[PDB]
Image (cartoon, rainbow over all chains, first blue to last red; front, side, top):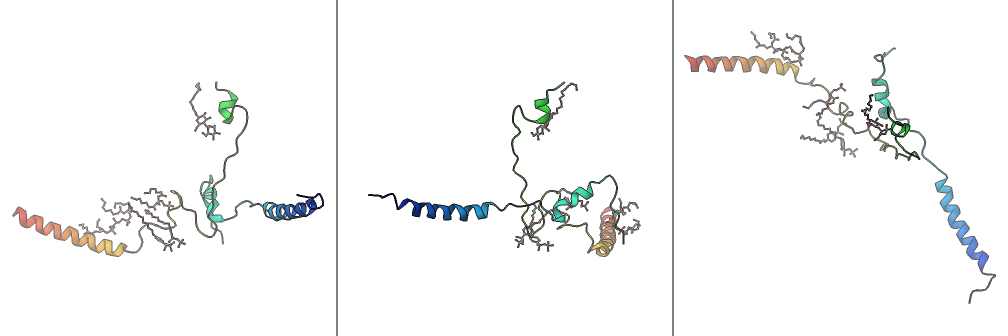
Length: 53
Length: 68
Ligand SMILES: CCCCCCCCCCCCO[C@@H]1O[C@H](CO)[C@@H](O[C@H]2O[C@H](CO)[C@@H](O)[C@H](O)[C@H]2O)[C@H](O)[C@H]1O
Ligand SMILES: COCCOCCOCCOc1ccc(C(C)(C)CC(C)(C)C)cc1
Ligand SMILES: COCCOCCOCCOc1ccc(C(C)(C)CC(C)(C)C)cc1
């Protein structure tokens, strides 16, 4: 009850689905740049921080 | 003294560690990130001087009256 010509339609559907998946999963989160997350890297330096202006 | 497995923390395969969450759009909340919310007392220092004087004086008054 399933002819062979109807298969590429299903293949098109699944290709659309997996492309909608991969266009999202191709994105990834980079390294964090918030200074509040890395202020202790500077707090723990071997010398005190110079606020130079 | 100790094997390289113990030093590196794995026998065969180094397992991935889940990184720390950041909570974008707000400050980190850790045991070391609390001075952002609680600084040293700075608002009622002059009231502290006055109240220490008055506390000393009232205590001395009532102690002397009790003793006498
Ligand atoms: C020196 C004279 C002869 C005596 C030798 C033996 C001395 C033993 C006492 C020192 C013990 C130190 O114990 C030390 O514990 C830490 C945990 O903090 C282990 O740490 C290990 O596990 C942690 C997490 O659990 C990993 O992230 C880390 O990469 C790995 O090193 C060290 O691998 C171990 O060496
Ligand atoms: C055992 O001791 C009890 C400790 O209880 C801690 C109470 O915590 C409640 C803190 O609630 C807040 C919430 C928000 C804030 C703001 C965001 C308003 C503070 C700000 C603007 C200074 C960052 C301050 C305190
Ligand atoms: C010496 O310190 C002892 C007590 O420390 C209390 C620290 O409290 C800080 C609490 O951190 C917060 C701050 C804000 C918030 C809210 C929910 C108010 C932030 C919001 C509205 C941006 C989501 C929650 C937790």
